[PDB]
Image (cartoon, helix red, strand yellow):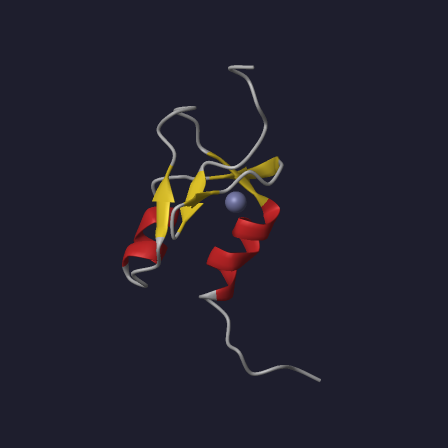
Length: 70
Ligand SMILES: [Zn+2]
């Protein structure tokens, strides 16, 4: 209904519909995306700050490295 524990992100125009958990979109997350110029916009329709755990890892991936570990 108006309530819906799902994401608030948009990627390339696909309004993310993955289920939302403990993950959210604080004013600190923004700067990590701005410094990376990703296609990750914000759904103002539900006017909420929840994200799916798939997107939670994505913004945490840009702080890591594509080089694997032992
Ligand atoms: Zn998402």
